[PDB]
Length: 342
Ligand SMILES: [Cl-]
Ligand SMILES: [Mn+2]
Image: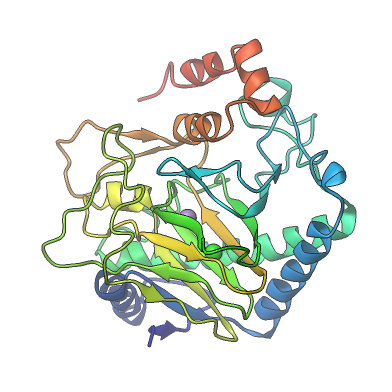
């Protein structure tokens, strides 16, 4: 049922690229999502990442819980810590943010959220880094095609995503263990572009655009999308399919396009067995600001580093990362980094 596209290796701006980008936009506007074909290498790397994830999740909780940092939000999140619309969600998560050594100038300077990933081991590290390198190449192709499909300069989005704050959430959902099967409630993702991969089990549902339906701007206080539409059709089951990733827009793409793209609502149902998946965020630079593309007189901006830092401080208010931001007043660095820019 979902539409599938094959991306060119290089996006150059030829008229065929523009046609493809238009078709990607149309698929998002119709279905909220599409598939992209993976080649043998992309597929191999995806499967290796899922295998590493499964092995890590079998480690004892005492070890998993030690994979945390007070410099970066990368690392482990136990089941039941994340909350959607007031209700705790079920997956355990390993988050991979930009892996910066303590010698990096941003880590030395104490920028919030910047530091080395607390990897469980080097084998897991290599599997996830190799996968994320491929995901990033796809993210850049997608963003060039999306700019072209809107008749924008080809580098409109990729100028923002140079050294972007790309990150991945590596998920394990438990089997169902009672009448409850809400693995994650309905929500929209805070990022720019989401590339999702899953194993063969099944559980992701997405909501297409619906004519006449009011959608909230989830980047605004007071317009949370959490829980909305959860018990009303339409919800499309994202059938596990060999040889594809799926792609949907996040909140920052909804903001930049003024709602011509909508951030795709989605939710996860627990299956009768455990399920592994990955959600990759292809993001602006920490220092970049998103802006409305089609409303030149609009003053509103989303500063990405501020957006991310505030999101994760709210997600994980007692994590040692959040404690150190507060103890050392690391949010002051964000204020400073804006000072002499246009
Ligand atoms: Cl998922
Ligand atoms: Mn999500």
